[PDB]
Figure 1 (cartoon, rainbow, N blue to C red):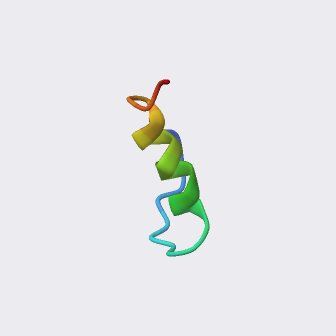
Figure 2: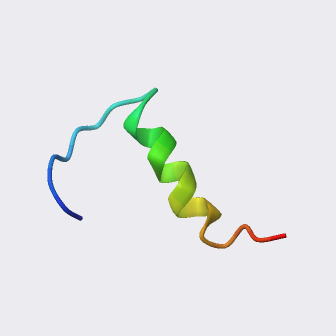
Length: 26
């Protein structure tokens, strides 16, 4: 939620992974 909203497939998505890590915490 900043700028640029490209669909992508094998790039930006990666960043999304981090958004899923927000919960991931040893």
